[PDB]
Image: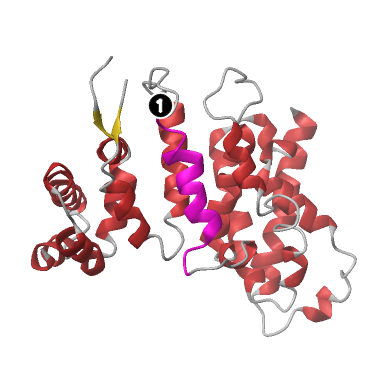
Amino acid sequence: ERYNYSKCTVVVRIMEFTTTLLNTSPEGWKLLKKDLCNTHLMRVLVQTLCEPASIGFNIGDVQVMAHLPDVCVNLMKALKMSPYKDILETHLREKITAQSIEELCAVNLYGPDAQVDRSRLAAVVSACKQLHRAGLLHNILPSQSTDLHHSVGTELLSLVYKGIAPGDERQCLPSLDLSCKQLASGLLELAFAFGGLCERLVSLLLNPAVLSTSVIHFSHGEYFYSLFSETINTELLKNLDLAVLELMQSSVDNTKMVSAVLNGMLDQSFRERANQKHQGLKLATTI
């Protein structure tokens, strides 16, 4: 309690200066020479980011331990355009967030082994979403064979669209704990932090495949839509022209699906219209 709370405030206060007094200057390398010894901030920073319970967030206390990320975020944005950039990139992308391990994290979701099962990717997504706040994410993942980041296009299908519904084995399909609902929704949310995903997403919304079950059948593409509705709708509502184009010209046998998402789009825009003064009139014009 005493030593942990005292060190919690100190390590956060060192991290704070490296942004707030230091890097927001016409030059700082007359100091970044003198501390070229520094892996020690960078390992503490990355462990703070990806497993905060390793230092200070062990205390579980919501006001302090939910603000701690914003220090890490703005320090990454400060070093994004420091000439020091490479030395964070030789840690983050190398240790806490290697490429293929995110596909290996698909082997156990919502399992019996609840003490240890799957918190390891909850760590990963909390870190890499905070890296999107900082903008480093598009380099902390390397680019792949097509305009969509293949690791993102593939986690969409492999960590959730395959894993959500046991239609291959037909052992009964699960009603979802808010834990696996919200977690899947966060993996989806992360996927739409990236570019190029729109033209694939339609084929998973308008999927003609029907689930089999207590014995009755219903659409897999519509099930995914009607379950994950919010995380889909905003990511059709940010990008109205090309989204409505695929929803009206590319859509086929569409009635049992386009009906739902065209209503959904209007409902969720109307829900946000309190801030979104413009976006409903854009949507209306485009349909």
Residue at position x 54%, y 34% in the image: 62
Q: Secondary structure at mark 1?
A: helix
Quarter of the figure that contains the C terminus = bottom left
Left or right, 25 with respect to 270, comes to right
Left or right, 57 with respect to 236, comes to right
The scheme the figure's colours follow is: secondary structure
x and y percentages locating residue 249 in the rendered image: 16, 64
The magenta segment is: 147-166
Quarter of the figure that contains the N terminus = top right
Q: Is residue 89 above or below residue 180?
A: below
Q: Amino acid at mark 1?
A: Leu
- Residue closer to the observer: 159 or 170: 170
x and y percentages locating residue 199 in the rendered image: 34, 62
**Residue lying farthest to the bottom in this orientation:** 26
x and y percentages locating residue 237 in the rendered image: 25, 58
- Residue closer to the observer: 118 or 281: 118
Label 1 crowding class (10 Å Cα cut-off): few <14, some 14-19, many 20+? few
x and y percentages locating residue 144 in the rendered image: 57, 66
Q: Is residue 274 above or below residue 213?
A: below
Left or right, 146 with respect to 84, comes to left
Q: Name the residue carrying label 1.
A: 178
What predominant SS class does the magenta segment belong to?
A: helix
**Residue lying farthest to the top in this orientation:** 214
Question: Residue 159 lies in magenta, yes or no?
Answer: yes
